[PDB]
Length: 165
Length: 165
Image (tube, rainbow over all chains, first blue to last red; front, top):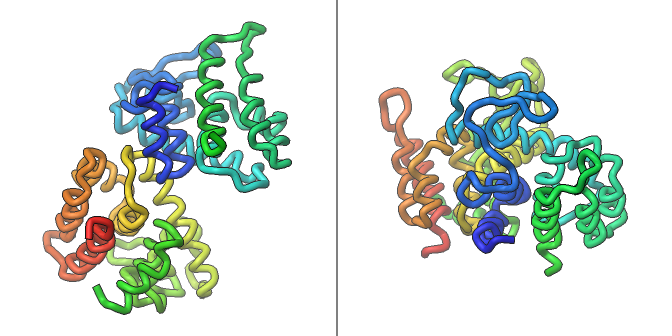
């Protein structure tokens, strides 16, 4: 991963999985992460309304220009939600890096997908290294493989396996 | 602080930042820490129901008597929440003493207040001395400086500055 991002994830470690994920999504500067940011609402490719760091919901004011602080508040809430949605399903102790990287993964890919993934089953069997490797299989959308996903998956993989080496 | 407590801090240091904060809140006995303990809902001065060592939610039963057991459940959860809400905002590496000190402070003053604060800004510019000193600015409410908050911030501060001697 870029060295600034690496250092960023390093300092977030004391802050636990949530903070780790927040670095992955927003990046060191808070605007150069694996997710885009947008201060004004827009419809995505599936026609869902979205703003800030990829935030969707029934609470988007279409006429509003959002601040950096609003965007960060909303991410916090959404990450807490991801945690709520997936942590029940992780039946084993994993390191904070691994947890944070799965948050970032699930943020992108959705809770359903994760619940039925092979990645989870390898987590629940204690195969951490094997779970982190499953990430590379998640680069396909519209029967095309995406350079942007393959990169994201590589970076989430590094962090997922951060403790090992 | 009181020696009764200065020791009991050090007692759960190896428990990490959560355990440091949780200590400051309950103190060794359970009432003799920074928060007020109460096993029946009372309406506080601003008219919010409150129970145990400061727990407020919508999850409160108005005639119920809570146990020493159920209040530990509420606190731990509440403190999980504080860590979720503030850590992503903390971009640098910090001692578990310092972090735990901040968990307590935010318990008291709220995530919003914290996210906009000068203190967090000093934290993130690496200035930990400068950070902890900012605790002292948080001793007013309703016009007046309170001696009780003046104490409470000196305590939180002491713990905040445990690394630097």
